[PDB]
């Protein structure tokens, strides 16, 4: 049984420290850009279809069908299509930064469709009250609607992070970096039973933690 | 303050809250409290929204402090909206901000100086007394408090007209006696021209100047309530009095 | 009926374009199963979801058959990807530096060919006499030029030329990026890694397998292979040419 | 009978809950009578009204309803008992995406009655209130008064044994109210006359209550019978409430 | 080049129909189970989160942790771990039915988490009312949870369907499943830009049709 303790600790430490570092930066940075640009687009989807602040049937229809296309079109295939544009922006095709770019594009379009829920669900009459007191549309969104759905936004970001984790592992085998780029080396190929149980353990503890953080804050911010 | 005209109408199974609001017009004079009365719903539970143009009518036009409103662009309509106060059948507030902060909210939209907001909220909170539990949230307090929150929210920006929708009438009469005393002072000092809806006679006789009595999106009568006496002439008016 | 396992690409291409119509002329209904993962095709063979599979090479069959104690055998070699080193950010071999970068496949056995070739370049030394079929970074006796190896997916190696100094290309992606296949700075003479058809060992004598083997050695198949897979390392059955 | 017994709901030092702590309190209500309940919103509009159903549990005290303790039943039998007792509420709480006629049918779906007797009781209690014409309409076709009748009808349908009200006609008009209360008096013809109710106002109470209780901060200061539409209060501070005449 | 592209496409005729015929089975079938068991799981979590029915603190925490552990656990690794069980149940591990089982497993947890949004976010009053009425928890699920929240469920179903389509590309590699296998062919191994553009256009149609269907259903429910 001690075979298991020795086989991992001696070699794997040296790689694990980098494989982890690559993983965190790739999830974190992609998430930030996804939540940022996804917010603005989600707002546009809502405010064009709101028919209260403003309206445009056509722009609403165009933006929805765009968002639909991009949400459903396959991510791995999109990354292969995005290699020239990616290299031209990043200055290279390989590394966590380049993956973070394509991840962020998927996450951008992913985010906004969620937030559509977050707005259609909200109580009507306070909108009429804001309009009754003559605020600019920008003030209504900026300094009302978020706080009212504040608990809703915490949940959405929590679930997006968990999604991007699975996506980052898929992104890493082709582009390099991440625990996926480890797992394919010690599973699928040169498979080792003991090394695989250690990666599984690390994931479990990390993914409880992020969710438990999310639920505690969301609960605090009712 | 005058209407030119208004109406708004609905097809079978078009089905908004009520059947049609008919061709109608009125003048409400300066420094005057004007009451609205009649059986429930009937477009009367809506009619006041048309004054603040919160429903666009199917017909007609309205003038308020000179300006005709229906022709206005939205950015001009903001100032018309800002100067006219309203309060409602439901409490219509920002759940996740405190009571005092809900009271600050319209004054944030007024763009008032931070200390002007702070002073005005402390003033209006104290005028209604609820400064004593203003650092508070809607689960913590009751509907009675929440009425005073509506009142203060409407009051604070010194609007030139108030368009009450049964806010003070919403409480039971015994509780109402202690609050009605407030509105009297507000009118005497600032000539607020306050317009009110009701389905109870008692409050009118103890507060108002003229009453429109109503049914089917239309007038039954307009009556003087002066002398604490409603000088009506129709039997429908007599039923509404009882 | 006959059931085949191949990877996607060149070996499944051999089955799709020529061998499949050849065996149907010979009365056999062929089913092809295509894989993108190395582990599943052999299991499916030993488990009899397949009757045969041409994706395994001589080193890979031995590991997986040993590790999983499988009832399988090779049968015949097949036309195999040459391996070769190509210009990247550096244009000729002599340009190599201490800390130069080389792009290589993340496969253990194809990494073993790469290691054997960098020893033939004399850039690294391997511990010669150690198992060639299972060579790795630890089997580098000395990284003579302190080369910065870059493990990648093989279909990315053609694009990597711009990102790395020299780029080993698998040969499965050299001739599909055929526009640059000629630019090889080095060539592979190693015969330790030939691709090999494989079956459950009990199947080795079957007439259907003899007809697969014959299809894989028919003159029509040779004409098709010369045309489709030009420059590939032939079976020693073909005289390795 | 109802017996109300040393009931309390003490809270924390922060006391950040729905209201300020409420004190150990007791009363008795009879088979033959109507009881009104009156104070200021400082005592709490809610008072202990939610706890009467046992939406809360006495920190001191106990609760006999129809002569049977409810704090002891402590089982699906207590829920079954709850199904048998009538109440209406300050908040309309109506389902939005089913017609209000089917919100009227919703309480009898709880009783599990045969669907034909459901249809019958429904039409009966619905036409007694007179909202049968606007029953098929969803809630985007209404005012408060319609919605009130809906709550009232929802309460009536079981012919429940005992009845509780929650300041209902604060936002309603007299002749509908008068006719509704005349229906409740007909319920006295049925097995029970017990009609417990809160209004902090006098107008209603003077018009038709039998008995009443006057209170502040969880202290009851007097109980008064009403006679010839007069309260006849003995209590001094009670008379500060009677000034609201 | 245009005529060369067009004339090429006609050759692939039968293969395209066989890839598409495969694809419907994977997505449709797996979705059904995902919506089925994910419902129960989300409900059970929610009732043990509340005092309605029975409040079980410990059970709630353990079950919640299990859902987070399984969502965030990597899809591709999970598929490879499932091999021996999958083989015994289905009688095979190759093909679209075996793959759809694995798709659906991921879907149970993802759908239960999605359900949780909608469940926790309902307005209190009607629940409090039926509870005051002494109604049994069965009646609460039978109508009360549904009446409004069913529109948010159409939204949840719509995003889930679109999600299973993306995962079907990744299973398309190992199971040889539908349009994922088709995109792995003449993609990394060979470069036929014409059939890529065709695959893109074919997907684009399916995307628009799915989201347009979801949008209309959710609009019409309220």
Image: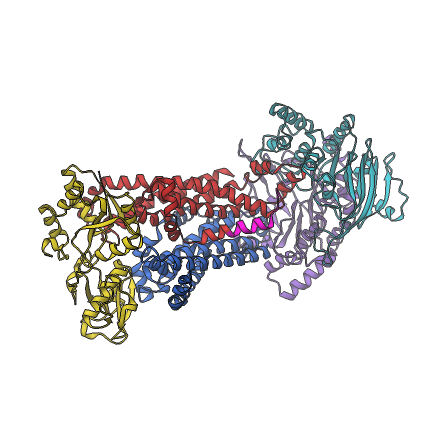
Chain colours: A blue, B purple, C yellow, D cyan, E red
- The quarter of the picture where residue A36 lies is bottom left
**Quadrant of image for the N terminus of chain C:** top left
D44 over D177 or under it: above or below: below
Q: Position of residue A90 (x, y in %)?
A: 33, 65
Task: Confirm whether the magenta stretch covers residue B103.
Answer: no
- The quarter of the picture where residue A101 lies is bottom left
Residue under the image location 29 percent in, 67 percent down = C137
E36 over A90 or under it: above or below: above
Residue under the image location 85 percent in, 35 percent down = D229
C27 over A164 or under it: above or below: above
> Which of the pair B127/A178 is nearer the observer?
A178
> Which of the pair E49/D168 is nearer the observer?
E49
**Quadrant of image for the C terminus of chain C:** bottom left
A170 over C218 or under it: above or below: below
What residue span does the magenta drawing correspond to?
Answer: E52-65
Q: Position of residue B82 (x, y in %)?
A: 60, 55
> Which of the pair E22/D242 is nearer the observer?
E22
Residue A101 horizontal side relative to residue C168, left or right:
right
Q: Position of residue D1 (x, y in %)?
A: 81, 34
| Count of numbered badges drawn on the protein | 0
Residue under the image location 23 percent in, 58 percent down = C59
> Which of the pair B108/E191 is nearer the observer?
E191
Q: Report the residue that reaches farthest toward the bottom.
A: C98
Residue D21 horizontal side relative to residue C88, left or right:
right
Q: Position of residue C234 (x, y in %)?
A: 13, 55
Report if residue A134 is visible in the image. yes
Task: Confirm whether the magenta stretch covers residue E55.
Answer: yes
Report if residue B234 is visible in the image. no
Q: Main secondary structure of the magenta part?
A: helix
């Amino acid at each position: 049984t001690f075979q298991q303790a020795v086989s991992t600790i001696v070699g794997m430490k040296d790689e694990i420290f980098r494989a982890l570092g690559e993983t965190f930066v790739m999830v974190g940075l992609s998430t930030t850009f996804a939540v940022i640009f996804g917010t603005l687009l989600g707002v546009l989807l809502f405010v064009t279809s709101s028919r209260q602040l403003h309206y445009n049937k056509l722009v609403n229809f165009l933006l929805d069908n765009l968002v639909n296309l991009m949400r459903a079109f396959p991510f791995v295939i999109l990354m292969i299509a995005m290699i020239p544009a990616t290299r031209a922006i990043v200055g290279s095709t390989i590394g966590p930064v380049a993956a973070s770019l394509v991840l962020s594009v998927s996450g951008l379009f992913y985010f906004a469709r969620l937030v559509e829920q977050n707005l259609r669900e909200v109580p009507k009459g306070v909108i009429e009250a804001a309009a009754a007191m003559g605020a600019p549309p920008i003030a209504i969104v900026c300094k009302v609607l978020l706080n009212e759905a504040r608990a809703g936004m915490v949940s959405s970001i929590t679930v997006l992070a968990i999604g991007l984790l699975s996506y980052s592992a898929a992104a890493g085998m082709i582009g390099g970096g991440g625990l996926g780029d480890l797992a394919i080396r010690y599973g699928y190929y040169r498979y080792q039973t003991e090394v695989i149980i250690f990666i599984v353990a690390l994931l479990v503890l990390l993914v409880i933690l992020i969710q438990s953080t999310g639920n505690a804050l969301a609960r605090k911010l009712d | 303050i005058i209407l030119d005209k208004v109406s708004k109408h609905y097809q079978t199974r078009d089905k908004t809250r009520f059947a049609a609001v008919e061709p109608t017009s009125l003048e409400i004079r300066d420094g005057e409290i004007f009451g609205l009365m009649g059986y429930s719903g009937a477009g009367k539970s809506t009619l006041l929204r048309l004054i603040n143009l919160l429903e666009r009518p199917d017909s007609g036009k309205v003038n308020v402090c000179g300006q005709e409103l229906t022709a206005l662009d939205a950015a001009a309509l903001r100032q018309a909206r800002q100067n006219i106060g309203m309060v409602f059948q439901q409490f219509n507030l920002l759940s996740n901000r405190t009571v005092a902060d809900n009271v600050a909210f319209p004054l944030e939209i007024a763009g008032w100086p931070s200390e002007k907001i702070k002073a005005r909220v402390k003033e209006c909170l104290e005028i209604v007394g609820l400064t004593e539990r203003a650092g508070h949230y809607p689960a913590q307090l009751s509907g009675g408090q929440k009425q005073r929150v509506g009142i203060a929210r409407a009051l604070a920006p010194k609007p030139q007209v108030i368009l009450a929708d049964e806010p003070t009438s919403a409480l039971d009469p015994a509780t109402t006696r202690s609050v009605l005393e407030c509105l009297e002072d507000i009118n005497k000092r600032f000539n607020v021209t306050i317009v009110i809806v009701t389905h109870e006679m008692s409050v009118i006789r103890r507060l108002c100047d003229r009453a429109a009595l109503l049914d089917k999106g239309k007038v039954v009568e307009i009556v003087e309530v002066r002398g604490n006496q409603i000088h009506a002439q129709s039997d429908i008016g007599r039923e509404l009095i009882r | 009926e006959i059931v085949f396992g191949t990877t996607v690409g060149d070996f499944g291409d051999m089955v799709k374009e020529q061998i499949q119509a050849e065996l149907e002329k010979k009365g056999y209904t062929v089913k092809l199963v295509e894989f993108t993962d190395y582990v599943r095709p052999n299991l499916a063979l030993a488990e009899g979801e397949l009757d045969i599979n041409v994706f395994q090479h001589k080193p890979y069959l031995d590991d997986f058959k040993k590790e999983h104690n499988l009832d399988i055998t090779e049968v015949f070699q097949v036309p195999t990807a040459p391996l070769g080193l190509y210009p990247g950010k550096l244009k000729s071999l002599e340009e190599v530096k201490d800390g130069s970068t080389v792009s290589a496949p993340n496969d253990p056995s194809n990494f073993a060919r790469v290691l054997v070739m960098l020893d033939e370049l004399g850039w690294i030394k391997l511990k010669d006499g150690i198992n060639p079929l299972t060579a790795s970074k630890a089997d580098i006796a000395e990284n003579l030029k302190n080369i910065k190896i870059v493990e990648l997916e093989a279909a990315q190696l053609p694009r990597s030329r711009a990102d790395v100094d020299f780029a080993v290309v698998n040969g499965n992606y050299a001739i599909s990026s055929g526009m640059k296949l000629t630019e090889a700075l080095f060539q592979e003479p190693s015969f330790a890694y030939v691709n090999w058809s494989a079956v459950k060992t009990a199947d080795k004598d079957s007439q259907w397998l003899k007809d697969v083997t014959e299809a894989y050695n028919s003159d029509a198949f040779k004409a098709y292979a010369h045309k489709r897979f030009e420059g590939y390392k032939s079976p020693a059955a073909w005289n390795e040419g």
